Image 1 (tube, rainbow, N blue to C red):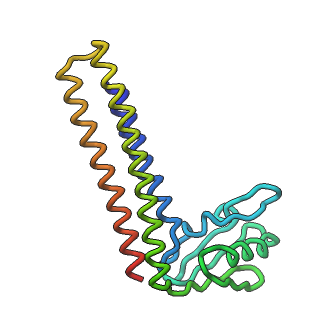
Image 2 (cartoon, rainbow, N blue to C red):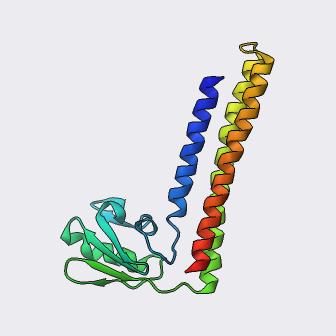
Length: 184
């Protein structure tokens, strides 16, 4: 019973952290390195997130400054940025890449709100399946008499509480990003 419950809880916390990260890939006012992470180049034959090939600095809310770890990667990196769906036109200063981030149109804003909610759905579905797996194990344990009925019943209640707490937390994360997106 313990194995099942503890692992489920850890997996759920991970899924919530994955959700956190995933949400951070959403273009927004208030720039951050996260929204550049799904931007890749061809790094010696392999598609590589540019967040791994450069340090990203965010001085102002709508100003990002990027420094390639290898100078000769600058052009490709900057090309991927401009070619990306962030809707930005980067500039170059010989060494660094400065990115001015325009205000999002209201149309694009609700488009991004929709992405945020889809990411939340994926994350909540994942947390529910983590629960299903642990619950079925609890069920197997009761059926095979490997633990007492009261004992398994208490574990079920606890598992539902943990599941619900993390679903709610995903919901909050989404509502927060939704807010960020309609803030500017």
